[PDB]
Image (tube, rainbow over all chains, first blue to last red; front, side, top):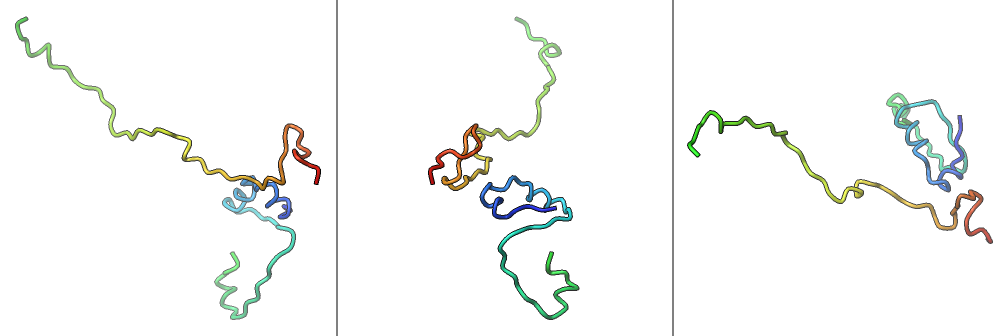
Length: 50
Length: 50
């Protein structure tokens, strides 16, 4: 699924996201975003990204 | 009146351990969108002459 971030921080977030995050459900996000590069594989196995 | 124990001895029904709260509300966490983004029953946008 999806959820425009632009409209999010505008609308004020209706815990829609808050709920999905809490409950763990496959989802996507959209808009401008800060990436962050890592290396030491480790990080991955440890699944830091979650 | 004479005194008769038996009849003066009553048992007691009392609840146990409350915690009384006043004011209430307070427990409410609430923020606000940025003014530039309002809306009435309208839903188009209150104050919309950019």
